[PDB]
Amino acid sequence: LYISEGLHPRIITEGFEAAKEKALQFLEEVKVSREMDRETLIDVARTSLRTKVHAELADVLTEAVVDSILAIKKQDEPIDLFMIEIMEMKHKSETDTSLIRGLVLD
Amino acid sequence: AAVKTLNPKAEVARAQAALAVNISAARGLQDVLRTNLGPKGTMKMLVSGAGDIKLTKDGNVLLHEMQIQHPTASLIAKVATAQDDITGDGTTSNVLIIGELLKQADLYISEGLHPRIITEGFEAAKEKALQFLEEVKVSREMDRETLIDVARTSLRTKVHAELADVLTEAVVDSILAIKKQDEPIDLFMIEIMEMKHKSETDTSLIRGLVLDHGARHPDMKKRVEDAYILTCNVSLEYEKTEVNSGFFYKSAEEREKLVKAERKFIEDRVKKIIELKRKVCGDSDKGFVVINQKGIDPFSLDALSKEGIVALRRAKRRNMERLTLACGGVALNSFDDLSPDCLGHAGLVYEYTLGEEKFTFIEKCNNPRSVTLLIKGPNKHTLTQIKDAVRDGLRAVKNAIDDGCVVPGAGAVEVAMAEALIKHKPSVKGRAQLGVQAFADALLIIPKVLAQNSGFDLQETLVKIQAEHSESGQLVGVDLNTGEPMVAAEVGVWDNYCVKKQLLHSCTVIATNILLVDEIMRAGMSSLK
Amino acid sequence: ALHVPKAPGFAQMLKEGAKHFSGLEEAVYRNIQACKELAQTTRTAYGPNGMNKMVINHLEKLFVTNDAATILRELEVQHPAAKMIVMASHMQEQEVGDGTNFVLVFAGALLELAEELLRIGLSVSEVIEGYEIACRKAHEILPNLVCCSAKNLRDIDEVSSLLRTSIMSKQYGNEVFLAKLIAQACVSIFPDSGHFNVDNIRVCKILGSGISSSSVLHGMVFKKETEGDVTSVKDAKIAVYSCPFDGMITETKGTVLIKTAEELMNFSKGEENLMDAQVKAIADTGANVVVTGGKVADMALHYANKYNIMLVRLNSKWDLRRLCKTVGATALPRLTPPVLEEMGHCDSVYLSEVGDTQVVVFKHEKEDGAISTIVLRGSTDNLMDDIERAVDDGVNTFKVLTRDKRLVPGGGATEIELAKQITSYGETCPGLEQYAIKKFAEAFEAIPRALAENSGVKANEVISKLYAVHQEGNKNVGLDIEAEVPAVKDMLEAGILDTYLGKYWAIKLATNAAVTVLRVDQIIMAKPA
Amino acid sequence: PVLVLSQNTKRESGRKVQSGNINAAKTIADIIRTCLGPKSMMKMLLDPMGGIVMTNDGNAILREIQVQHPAAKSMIEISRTQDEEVGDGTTSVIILAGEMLSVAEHFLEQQMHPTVVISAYRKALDDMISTLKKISIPVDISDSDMMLNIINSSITTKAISRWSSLACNIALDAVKMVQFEENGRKEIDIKKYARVEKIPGGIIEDSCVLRGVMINKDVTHPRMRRYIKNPRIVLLDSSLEYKKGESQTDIEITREEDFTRILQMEEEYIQQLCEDIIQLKPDVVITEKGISDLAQHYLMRANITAIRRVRKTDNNRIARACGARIVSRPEELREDDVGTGAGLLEIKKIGDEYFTFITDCKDPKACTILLRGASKEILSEVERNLQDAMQVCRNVLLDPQLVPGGGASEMAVAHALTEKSKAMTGVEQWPYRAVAQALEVIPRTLIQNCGASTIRLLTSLRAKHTQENCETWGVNGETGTLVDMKELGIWEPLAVKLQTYKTAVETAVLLLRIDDIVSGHKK
Ligand SMILES: Nc1ncnc2c1ncn2[C@@H]1O[C@H](COP(=O)(O)OP(=O)(O)O)[C@@H](O)[C@H]1O
Ligand SMILES: Nc1ncnc2c1ncn2[C@@H]1O[C@H](COP(=O)(O)OP(=O)(O)O)[C@@H](O)[C@H]1O
Ligand SMILES: Nc1ncnc2c1ncn2[C@@H]1O[C@H](COP(=O)(O)OP(=O)(O)O)[C@@H](O)[C@H]1O
Ligand SMILES: [Mg+2]
Ligand SMILES: [Mg+2]
Ligand SMILES: [Mg+2]
Ligand SMILES: [Mg+2]
């Protein structure tokens, strides 16, 4: 919009850099530091799964994902998502997706 | 899609596709033509498929010569062709304003605004802008100085500066010569002849006529001082009878008699001409020039040469009127009762040979209501360029005379109309204010491109100009040598009120229709085969 | 201006042979049309009066059937939405075994009515909401539509009366015979535990006589011959080996390293004496029949003939496992004589000739066992395959009844009651969801309509009669196919019943498929490799 | 190969053929579905001649597209039929036919016979006609304001809507001037005697209808006058040249004077023709054929202005406008054949061309509509819209009955048909009520193209039309709301809506009767 009016892209990118700096600052200011409780994690996982799948399946997958993470997580120790297997079975309805507190070998 | 289920080889651009296609083509045309605008513009070279060269800065010529096969480009070329046929100038600005209207409308349509609402804003802004134009137009007594300034504003954009300073006086004098008080100007009465021998600054105004042919008898004089001009439309060559006739004779003597007799009909017209010549020129003091719209056979040419008459044949249907207005005689379709009142006078008639071509000058008429512009130049493409430029200049001066008003130039009216539109915008109901804003930002493309072409910063220059126009209210535009604001009416940069009005009208109309296009479709035979 | 260019953006960046569809018209309506075409391809096979189709696949193999899932598999469905509906039908076949044509019909009907609603002005989101709410209501209702229950799966007359309906749609003319056969087999292999395995019903198709010469056999049949001289055995003591009937050899390369004429002279005699000892130990355990999953050696065959043992070679490992399950034996990986528990028993093992075919029969006399075989006779391989599909339908119905013993009335009675109740629910539901609920209800009418259309009567009269009777109160009334005119009768009293679980899963899967097809909005196909 | 029919003869039959025809028809409908109503959008069509057609007119679109399915061919033909008959409704008819075929597809899938469906459709058509004639209202065609409102209600849906008042006045003036009666036979021929001349450039706001005619012509000789303030005009079908005879008139010359005598005889013949013309003392002479230069000489000597080669149609319009009578033998010229009635002959330069005006006539029974605008395409669209407007004005002057627009008429008729269907007890009540509900597509389409909620608005409208005196209620195509047409002003000609309904129903009947396509066979 501004380069067609003869503005130089170098100047536009300088403005981009300034705005990026200020935006990162404002982001650090507005972030909400919260004790990560099951309810907060449920809201987060819902916010993602409701965008990615149907609403009822999202209400199922939310509890599934949050419980899985709250199960394979050790206090102050990076979460190894490899320790959450993901097995697919092709027989029943999609709302039967569950969390097995164990393992399922194929 | 729907059309493609019935005609499988069908091409279709729907809703958003259609708009993207049209706006892209319009912006492409604008991108090409941006450089034509103004005297600081750049000349483009155009090479035909045969290799012929064209040097042009004219928007219409550039459009028609570019190699384009786009439907939107065809639409805009047609709008420019109408602009050129009716006004002679404004084609580049027309294309630019169309492209910028489309761009400024896409700016808001990409954000989900409807093009119908944008077009409502376009129409409101068009109305208000036409009003403001009528308000700012300068109604002026069209004197030679004003016409000179107008023709300068056109010719300096179309050609080089010294050649523009020559063509200015040439064009203004030509129009001020073929112009009768309160009588629409017939530009046909300005002949335009090109000669390809001398420099381009030798282009002059002959206060008379220049025919692209001369006498076909060698013994005929090449220069005549005090000439009676006989403008005729009578065949002086052998004419066969309508009904098939044929000659029948029984002896070579009878054949000879029939050969002498078959020409008596044309000999009689030659005798009438010769008798008029003898009756009006009792001696060799004056001269006598016959100019025939039709042919003259060698026998008639010999008969006229023997009596000292200069006969030109196969003149032009327009040269009949041009000669009757320059010399001052009567053009004849018959020699039934020809009299000395049927003759015109030219204080000089002579011939000019240039390689294989001949020219005949008819000058020193008393008060010729028809003249000719002799386009001299070293190249065919130079001559074509000067022809285009003088067309532009003639149209400009004619329009400035017709519309006794004249509008300031250099983007001044565009700036002022943008400001007026922006001050009027709140009075518009709904989101058509956005269409109005788009119209204003589109009108602002003329000063923007003028600055861009003179080598200045569009935003900085436009801000300076708008600030100066807002503080003072004076109509200011771009000074192409300093980038500063300048008063166009004081510095002599004038535009045609008719041209600006036609711009507003036609650009608004075509942009509205393009914005309202929602489907481009080729589902016909695709060829006449 | 004779070509529409691709619009800037995705249309230009798209690959060569790729296609992009977007919107209700290019994507949704074309998907619905494809699914409707699919439902039309399979509609004429629904019900007892359904006609067979002869589909030839790309391998030039011929299938003559009216089994929807089989027809779909052997068709090369290439439209992706139709592929998804076929995926739903195949999931129904996997989960239940019967109802695939119901799934197809219902999905196509739901999609047609969804197109209708989208045209009247509903949004895909609202249509999907209403379809889901109506599927939930239907699932809530069906348990109340359950009319009878099995009450016993160890009987042979009741089980036949229960399987007759499922094996009536296929093979309508002769279904009592087939229900007798399949009931005998299912109750033979039904253990005291409630678990029932459909793989324990084996089907042997032998080309001869006719479907009425078919029989059930408590045991196993193999189109094999015996390796040795013995062909019959009356008190079988089968010993089963997964290893060949040869001397065990090393998995590492073995070499006979001879260094003396004595070793050379004695090697072969020692080898054969070893083989004789092995086979004599096997015979001395009492085994009179040996079944090897591998190959047979000439010396071992010699000694089996010497010691009067019937040798059988089963190339397949599933066949070997099923024989072990049948006779109560254990496959030994070594040629060691079996212990008293590893041995199997059969009341008879003999070689017979059913038709042109030679067969080895392991036949129990008791009316039980772990595996039962249905020997299908027939005049055509295609006919026998169709009867095998009908047998599979009956067996899957038996398993569905072992899972859930509840039954709903057939012949369109449950569908009509569902339609009525869901219409009454939608008439109460306010908001824009009522249109979609009522269309979901009206979709059920497609089932009795298809039944009537194939019976050869006016579906409109049939459906009006059904609605009238179900309004007056009879929920077990459905259409009578044994009537040249539109007629109706008590499906329960007639014995025409479906499985609650079958209907449940069919409705669920059809609704899910329709809703997914609707949830699709853009399609980006790649260039077909 | 021993065939019975030639290869390339492919024969389809049955429900596949029926569904194919119905899908082709409703596809033709879906092509132009969005071009209905006041808020429609333009379409840019690409001609086979490198041309462009930017339009909203259903018939223009269907005329520019090419198809191969015979059902689509039939739909294009019925659009052409509607356009030629009434000159409006070219997409309403297409949409109605598509909807009727769509709703008949239902009954066809359900084992109903096409003849049963067709008889039901014909019953419904008769009752539609009855209901329209009942709800129609008369018009006082002497009320210029009423006529201007009718023309606005007909052109509001087109590009010229921005210049609605101008176009309405132009169309009304043109039709009222072309209205002509002779021997007790009224005739509004707006195709031969209302001419549209498109001159690109200028501005549309200066477009006008002339009290006369206009041609693209100049004087034959620049000594002729270009301005005459009360011209007496003569029109000729014959050449004022000396042409040959019909027979083998070969001459044979043996004497000397005979050649010259023959050429002088030709000249004297031209003189005698010109004298036969001058004897009537005209000011202007207009010919469809040539005029020799000697004839020009004699006419100029008589102070006559001549125009050389005019078209036969332009000459007929000049006759109707200035009150002259075309002649073919100047010897047979009479004062009654001379043209008095023109108030001014002017020949002015528009751009770089010379145009001849014969305007200022009194009681001119012919006219020229001079259209000016931005480009040939814009002016072609303006001309098409003006053709629509004039055809509507003509339809009104012929049948002064009006019906309400905005879909009000469609909803009124649908309601009347639903009410009449309750007495029907046979099996045709269902297709009858189906076409009744298939009429709702017009207001449905209006709502869709304005961008409002079809479900809600159509429900509210069907409910409004169940009350007693609400058959005038319709929808706005500009806001998406229900209004009374008595208050909005959108009133269509009863003739237009009758032709629409009739053509739609008959097209449906035809395509339903059709089965068993055959093809390939070569004429
Ligand atoms: N000497 C000048 N100084 C500033 N502006 C000028 C001058 N001459 C012309 N212009 C402006 O340049 C614009 C474009 O001129 P020109 O190229 O002749 O018209 P077009 O772009 O339509 O061909 C005109 O609107 C005029 O106002
Ligand atoms: N004797 C009968 N009379 C009426 N309807 C029957 C009879 N037997 C079966 N049906 C109906 O036919 C349908 C079964 O058709 P079928 O082709 O098996 O469909 P699917 O294979 O999808 O279950 C059932 O809905 C049942 O109600
Ligand atoms: N302003 C308006 N509001 C609502 N409906 C209108 C309006 N103007 C016209 N209509 C209706 O739109 C219908 C079709 O308009 P038009 O596009 O001119 O005809 P067609 O669809 O045949 O081209 C007419 O029946 C008329 O009743
Ligand atoms: Mg996300
Ligand atoms: Mg210019
Ligand atoms: Mg079944
Ligand atoms: Mg109309």
Image: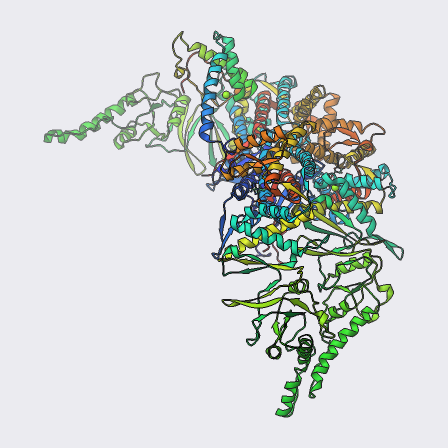
Relative to B402, D133 lies left or right:
right
Relative to the observer, which residue lies in front, A92 or C482? Answer: A92
Give the total of numbered labels.
0
Residue D437 sits above or below residue B521 on the image: above
On the question of residue C360 being in view, the answer is yes
Relative to the observer, which residue lies in front, D16 or B258? Answer: B258
Residue D177 sits above or below residue C92 on the image: below
Residue B304 sits above or below residue C419 on the image: below
- Across and down, in percent, residue B414 comes to 61, 36
Relative to C87, D234 lies left or right:
right
- Across and down, in percent, residue B85 comes to 63, 51
- Across and down, in percent, residue D85 comes to 77, 49
Relative to the observer, which residue lies in front, C417 or D229? Answer: D229
Tell me the quadrant of the picture where the C terminus of chain D can be found. bottom right
Q: Quadrant of ligand 6?
A: top right
Q: Quadrant of residue B311?
A: bottom right
- Across and down, in percent, residue C76 comes to 51, 38
Image color mode: rainbow
Instruction: Tell which residue pokes out farthest to the right in this image.
Output: D184
Residue C405 sits above or below residue C458 on the image: above
Residue at point 47%, 42% (across, down): C60
On the question of residue D65 being in view, the answer is no
Relative to D263, C9 lies left or right:
left
Q: Quadrant of residue D432?
A: top right
Relative to the observer, which residue lies in front, D198 or D393? Answer: D198
